[PDB]
Image (cartoon, rainbow, N blue to C red; front, side, top):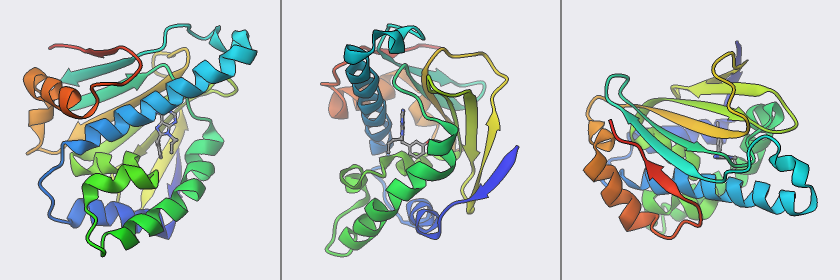
Length: 207
Ligand SMILES: CCCCn1c(Cc2cccc(OC)c2)nc2c(N)ncnc21
């Protein structure tokens, strides 16, 4: 288990997301689904010129899996996945500029729902989750588990869990007062409202 500090701008973003009073928390789900859709587009595009990139799984889809016993909502995709370098370094580097922009827009009276326009929508997970675990497998790399409860650090370990072929699972460990996002009718409503035209099957699992 390796522990890393977020870049200061990302930690500041996460604290803003956690601390700002903002009731429209449900938008976290469309930001994660949007990320999954971009990742699926990416592997789909890469496969057109190298069909072997689909040896790790041809099916291109999104699963939403609520688990009341564990209090988690998991967004699974079979998209391109992330490398260790993505997790530790590259995503944060990319996230640096979007963070500043977003934080700037927030006076000029943007609101948190617009976070996705700045390429940092992943962090809106922290509107509803006390802890986020990301399990991910990219073709050129091993399977990894990233985790963070915010507070300025995250961990990365090689994952010994169930091998996943290729793709990413974002496991949201929900805050005590956010269990509505475990309810089928609530998830269905949100997907219909914000993610109704995603170009991949989204299967909402039931409990
Ligand atoms: C900024 C988008 C790329 C990183 N990314 C994201 C957001 C993202 C940002 C920062 C960290 C993170 O995982 C720990 C994930 N979701 C992805 C996905 N489902 N598949 C592939 N890559 C993903």
